[PDB]
Each structure stands twice: as structure tokens, then as C-alpha cells.
Image 1 (tube, each protein chain N blue to C red):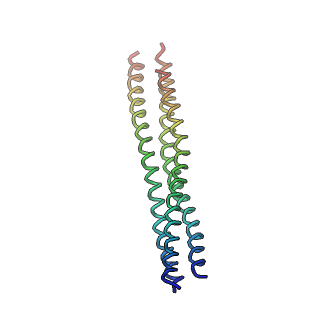
Image 2 (spheres, one colour):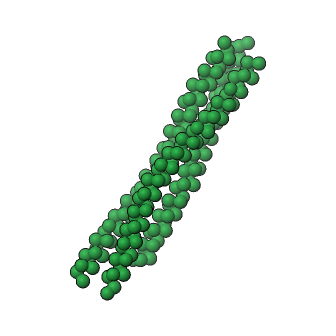
Length: 54
Length: 59
Length: 61
């Protein structure tokens, strides 16, 4: 009607989009933890084999 | 009717972006996980050689 | 119209967002990767050292 309309819509875009950026980042970071845990545990196992051998 | 049309464009386009964001990021993670695993596979071979070397020493 | 200014606004802000999320998440991965690269380098080094000493000890006897 339309200034107050554009304005309201823009504000909706703003909150929504911002909550999406944060969500993507949490979700990807989680994944990254899940994958990198497997590498850390493998590494933990290897130094422990080494120490035992020594 | 317009406001409803903007907002529902926002919801749809936002939902697709979050998905593309995660999908790309994860793909990059996977590439980095593989590069590390290449390293770990090597290290484990050297431990396996060192191990056989150590039981040669005994004597 | 008003559906055109609000929709182009939404596309531009969605665009910047997508790029920001991927960038930030990849920084996260990069940092964790470095940390682990660090832990690997050290272990590699000790192993190389221990192979050198053991091999030399073997040839000597």
C-alpha cells in the first residue's frame, strides 16, 4: 500500500535470513565435529600404540 | 495479498539457501577429512614398519 | 511494484547469506584441520626420528 508494506516485508527477510545464516553455520559445524572426531580418535589410537611400543 | 507474497518468497528462498550453505560446507569438510585421512594412513604404515623394526632389534 | 523491491531485496540478502554461511563454516573447518595437522606433524617427526635410530641400531648389530 505500500511503503509500510515493503518496510514490513524487508524486516521479515531480515530476521529470517539472519536466523538461517546462524542455523547453516551450527549445522555445518556440527558435521565438522562429527567427522573430525573420527580423525582425532584414530590419532589418539596411534599415539597410544606408539607409547605402548616404546 | 502482496505482503503475503513477499514473506512466502522469503520462506522458500531462505529454506533453499540454508540447504545450499550446509551442502557446500559439508562438501568442503569432506575434502579436508580426506586430506587428513591420507596423512593418517601414512603415519599408520610408519608405525607398522617401526613395530617390525623393534622386534628385529631383539636380538 | 512493491512486490519487486521486496523480492529483489530478499534475493540480494539471501545471496549474501549463503556466501557468509559457507565462509564462516569453512573457517571453522580450517581451524580444526590446522589443529589436527599440528598433532600429525609432531607424530610424523617423532616416528621419523625413531625409525632413524632403530634402523641405525639394527645395521650396527
